[PDB]
Image: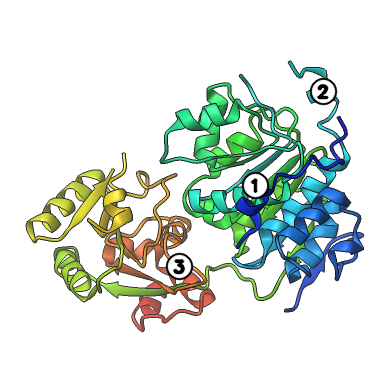
Amino acid sequence: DDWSKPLPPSERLEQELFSGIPVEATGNNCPPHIESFSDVEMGEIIMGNIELTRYTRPTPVQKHAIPIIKEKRDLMACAQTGSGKTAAFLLPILSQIYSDGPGEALRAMKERKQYPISLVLAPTRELAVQIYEEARKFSYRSRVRPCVVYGGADIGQQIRDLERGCHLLVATPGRLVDMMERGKIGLDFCKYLVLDEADRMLDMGFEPQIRRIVEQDTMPPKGVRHTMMFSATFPKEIQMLARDFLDEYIFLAVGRVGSTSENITQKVVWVEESDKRSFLLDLLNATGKDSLTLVFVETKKGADSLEDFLYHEGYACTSIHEEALHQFRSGKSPILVATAVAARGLDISNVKHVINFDLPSDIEEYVHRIGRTGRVGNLGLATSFFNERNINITKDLLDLLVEAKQEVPSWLENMAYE
């Protein structure tokens, strides 16, 4: 029917949901920013829900991004967490879907598989649920039904959830590919693609899954679908990702934005192989309570040997190469030993200290690894063990450390010069 007319209100559900800076824009014909939500026609359903959420004026990122998405322009937005990114894309997306109906395709075949009108990819369960929870608020009294799926949980409840109707899907890339392989999700009619915290999604190694979802299946190509990318940082790989995924897009800088995470203190120490375990014990002994430590080693056998060592020294630790992660979630075993390939696509959360026991051969991988720590709330630590085996990344590491404005070892530079 008409999706602009609000359904009758449920006050039980109303209680459940609603009871709780410089910006530069670059691109062609960028729509003017708004000062007020009413400065754009977002319809009765959205405006009603905005009042219930007790939001008055739009945040800086919302002031610029909303009229941009409203005009169906692709968006590359560089903004930090807590900016109000979620409502910045949810509000105008849901608005359009209220104005436009479900579409000719959905209306022509309404009679397992669900075809979401909008897809929102997120790196973690935490962020996905936050986006979903706000999607519920703004979809209140509407015919749009948001669903959320993520890894590290029973896929059965999620599948049964999808079957009950899904127009907007919030998903972690890994679980989504699982849903597509099971024929439970089709992307044929996905007109709104949002990638939230894309730099973190690449840090966790979701890029093949992301390119599998966007470029290798049935999702409409750029210029047909409308795509929005949100990233706190703008490194090379994000730039290339935006070039691939976005079409004639506006770039948004909602403040200071660079190539590096900003919230990671990087320490590079020279440690010979035979001293690494002793140096590691010293680090662990200086590790406070409450703190979760992540330790990267290069090979699988290395992880095995290191884990055995730590247990024999009486350290509460677990390894990855299930969920050795409730053991890590909780802090039963606050030390996680892992290879990069095995931590890939896994939601390793609240790591305060990352230790590169072994360094990788590619500087890109180093950035992904240290990205496992650091949030706007608290500064994260990345300690890396370096020796003659890592000489061939000297120049690239040095270059990263200066760009990240980190302390540079007085010897690191001298060995690069060779």
The answer to which of 206 and 134 lies nearer the viewer is: 134
Who's the residue at 61% across and 70% down the image?
Answer: 258
- Circles 3 and 2: CB distance less than 8 Å? no
Q: Residue 31 vs residue 106: left or right?
A: right
In this rendering, the label closer to the viewer, 1 or 2:
1
N-terminal label among 1 and 2: 1
The answer to which of 156 and 267 lies nearer the viewer is: 156
Residue of label 1 = 13
Disc assigned to residue 374: 3
Indicate the secondary structure of the residue bearing disc 1: helix
Category of crowding for the residue at label 3, using alpha-carbon neighbours closer than 10 angstroms: few (below 14), some (14–19), many (at least 20)? many
Residue of label 2 = 107
Residue 149 in percent (x, y) is at 53, 39
Instruction: Give the quadrant of residue 256.
Output: bottom right
Residue positioned most to the left: 312
Indicate the secondary structure of the residue bearing disc 3: loop
Category of crowding for the residue at label 2, using alpha-carbon neighbours closer than 10 angstroms: few (below 14), some (14–19), many (at least 20)? few
Residue positioned most to the bottom: 410
The three-letter amino acid code for the residue at tag 3 is Gly
Residue 123 in percent (x, y) is at 53, 50
Q: Residue 371 vs residue 36: left or right?
A: left
N-terminal label among 3 and 1: 1
Residues at marks 3 and 1, CA–CA distance in whole angstroms: 36 Å
- Taking 412 as reference, is 159 above or below it? above
